[PDB]
Amino acid sequence: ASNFTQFVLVDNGGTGDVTVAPSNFANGVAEWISSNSRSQAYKVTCSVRQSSAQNRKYTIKVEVPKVATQTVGGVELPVAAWRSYLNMELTIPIFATNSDCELIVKAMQGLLKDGNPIPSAIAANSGIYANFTQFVLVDNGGTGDVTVAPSNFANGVAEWISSNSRSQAYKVTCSVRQSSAQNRKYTIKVEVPKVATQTVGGVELPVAAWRSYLNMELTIPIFATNSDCELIVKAMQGLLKDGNPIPSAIAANSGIY
Amino acid sequence: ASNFTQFVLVDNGGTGDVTVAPSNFANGVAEWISSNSRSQAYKVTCSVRQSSAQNRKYTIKVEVPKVATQTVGGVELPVAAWRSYLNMELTIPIFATNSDCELIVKAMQGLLKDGNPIPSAIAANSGIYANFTQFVLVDNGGTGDVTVAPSNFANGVAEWISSNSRSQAYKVTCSVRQSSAQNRKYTIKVEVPKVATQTVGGVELPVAAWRSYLNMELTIPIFATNSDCELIVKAMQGLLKDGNPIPSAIAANSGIY
Amino acid sequence: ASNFTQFVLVDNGGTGDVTVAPSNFANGVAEWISSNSRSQAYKVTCSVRQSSAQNRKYTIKVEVPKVATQTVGGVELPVAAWRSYLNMELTIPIFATNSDCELIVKAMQGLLKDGNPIPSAIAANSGIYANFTQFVLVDNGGTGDVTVAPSNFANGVAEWISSNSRSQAYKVTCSVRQSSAQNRKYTIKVEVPKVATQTVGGVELPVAAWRSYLNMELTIPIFATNSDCELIVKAMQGLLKDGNPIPSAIAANSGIY
């Protein structure tokens, strides 16, 4: 309920906090503003939309403006010269118990943790970026964890499904390419499956609702570098961080308000 | 660091050692020469090239010239009548711990060991050659080993993924065919996955960077026989042998210099 | 009194010299040849040409041979088994004063000397040398540095960018590619910018007024052993250091004065 609390997007350390005021957006989505004007601040969207018939989506965008003086006037107009668009339509179950979403929430914070894969990849912007990595999607805590390795490499578009079948494990996809004369994209689809209401496979399973389709389109301009890209990552993880309104909504099978 | 040490390519036994002096090649690659002229010696390349966005490659070639008097002059011109081209663009992770590459290094020496599959196959040149075999890719030592059997046989182009999912195990491919009036090829792709920073699946996994695409194109001329082909194999294994500069580079996520 | 004459270039210890005498210029294309035998001579070019109305392009190719012996038909024919192709196209605008070119030359030749992170690739395994990271290059006295970090490789084309601003960054490329069945070609371009200020529209936009284009294509056959490339690199970079008869033209009035 009303998880609209002013949470810090980028946990830099206290200085220059990208603190974002909640409560906003029109026709079905969410928002979280930072302390500046309508051209240099950070955008943080999050909408709930019943994708199909048994699987509801979660469109969640997050902008990462480059805080630099505009080069089109020579005045003090605060605006970004380029932005790091972060899209992610995370599908999800609904009639399953509350602990099912916790499994998917950790499946988002664990995807971006301090000293982990993607977070330290897209952060250097080059000797590592774009996408395909590994991480225990569900960080349960010593027992019940989900391991997930890789295999195929067709046309440079990978697809990884966990320690189960090619039709019953935590799958994730992606791809990068120079779409035009200036930008690039990170189509990191993270189809997060659900496996809750269970101890360790103790029959009391009766789970419900099938999958999620976390399709992502992270456009990163060629004007970025190492430093500005670590900020892009901190925007992705500071998005789905425990206790924050973005993942907490996705935790109770609920929006925000 | 500077793994450029004179290592013996073919471990024949001391006589006629194909010892190769290191330190060479232009515009991004490596070399290791043998004691002769520029037409009968053995070539041993190895380049590092960031294939995509999160997966860096390892183009590694190795020539196997037939030490026979040239049949185009009747003089003492030392040159090969035919060569056994060995190509292998081995992709790989980078921001993962040093022990991740050890897993992939053994995944190359174990692929060619004394009294094993491929090494005793391509060696007889006929009742066994070309490709598709098995071997514990990662030779850990009694615990944590990776078993990997087979299944499909579509159009004669096999694909084998290990004891996991069709999207999360050690996969490898290949194929052979008479490309022209005189040569043949061994398109032995060995897509080596990574699974490090872990005991035996003890949660402390947090691994990173996805897969490798060790595409291979081993062209073997129809003028070869049993004896000259064992030398071709010893060139493949003496390439990725522990302690040698080729796999040692691939062991520390590094080149040579 | 005659300029463009027999000069000195690539050398090692005391045995064979490489005096490059003059030869042709037909239709605006300089050319230098060495000793008695042309089939073993060191070809080099140079031509002035204004590309449009605000620029001045150039073309300085270089073919480095090999003192081998092709015996075909019972005759020992002294011919090169391969040749280099160091072709540096450089565009210099009219607006760019006579104080930019001096620092451009030491940035093109002063980019690949005898092991720099870019040309060490042209002399050893790590054709990146460093798992491809932030390296050093062109410098002068103690004021501004040029740390060249990584950036892109899409479709097999390495690329390095420097500091904060891309419009003032030092781009550089590198890609492995086997041209046919008996050769190995490469491509290492280089764009050297200028820390100028284009004020158009009242804004001081930090952008380069021009960029260099040191593109060295090098073909190395499979027959050529791992002892030719070492002496090829010191012949391409070891051709234009910081005033050699060929690159002194790239730093002063002297074409070959």
Image: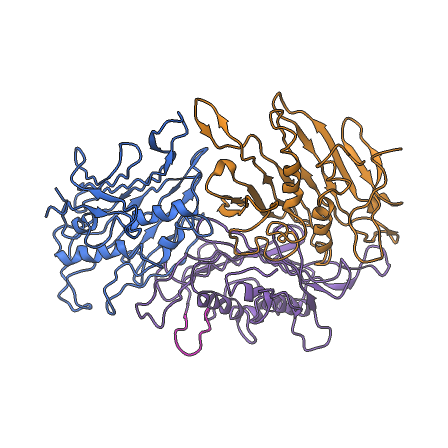
Chain colours: A blue, B purple, C orange
Q: Is residue C88 above or below residue B13?
A: above
Q: Return the residue found at the far top.
A: C53
Identify the residue shown where x is 37% and y is 40%.
Answer: A219
Along the viewing direction, whichever of C243 and C177 lies nearer the viewer: C243
Quadrant in which residue B95 is drawn: bottom left
Magenta stretch: dominant SS? Answer: loop
Quadrant in which residue B211 is drawn: bottom left
Is B214 left, or right, of A212 in this rendering? right
Quadrant in which residue B14 is drawn: bottom right
Along the viewing direction, whichever of A79 and A159 lies nearer the viewer: A79
- Residue C105 drawn at (x, y percent): 66, 39
- Residue A25 drawn at (x, y percent): 18, 35
**Which range of residues does the magenta coloring cover?**
B137-147
Is B141 covered by the magenta stretch?
Answer: yes
Q: Tag count in the figure?
A: 0
Identify the residue shown where x is 72% and y is 58%.
Answer: C225
Q: Return the residue found at the far left.
A: A1
